[PDB]
């Protein structure tokens, strides 16, 4: 799929200091603690860091990451939501 391709570029866009900085903010909703939070909480982690995903983008991005089957977002795949939203917030 194109998600695995947008993943490598999504993490590379953020530096080591930003990746570790977003790690604690993203794990704020890690109910299980497996490097992933609820796809619905994906809007909170983006806002808690400083970005602002519109509600239309949250539902469109959640359904895209909800196709995995578990209903959660992985840190490596979620990094695309962080950079793609920060590309405008930055």
Image: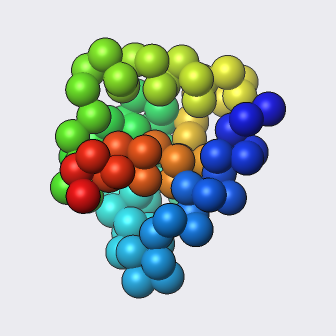
Residue, far bottom: 17
Occupied quadrant, residue 84: top left
Residue in the foreground of this view, choosing between 81 and 71 = 81
Residue ID at (47%, 26%) = 61
Residue ID at (35%, 57%) = 28
Figure check: 60 above or below 7 = above
Residue, far right: 1
* Residue 64 appears in the figure: yes
Residue in the foreground of this view, choosing between 42 and 7 = 7
Q: Is residue 29 left or right of residue 89?
A: right
**Quarter of the C terminus within the rendering:** bottom left
**Quarter of the N terminus within the rendering:** top right
Residue ID at (20%, 55%) = 50
Image x and y of residue 34, in percent:
61, 56
Image x and y of residue 36, in percent:
55, 49
Occupied quadrant, residue 70: top right
Occupied quadrant, residue 73: top right
């Amino acid at each position: 799929a194109s998600m695995t391709d947008q993943q490598a570029e999504a993490r590379a866009f953020l530096s080591e200091e930003m990746i570790a900085e977003f790690k604690a903010a993203f794990d704020m909703f890690d109910a299980d603690g497996g490097g992933d939070i609820s796809t619905k909480e994906l809007g909170t982690v983006m806002r808690m860091l400083g970005q602002n995903p519109t509600k239309e983008e949250l539902d469109a991005i959640i359904e895209e990451v909800d196709e995995d089957g578990s209903g959660t977002i992985d840190f490596e795949e979620f990094l695309v939501m962080m950079v793609r939203q920060m590309k405008e917030d930055a």
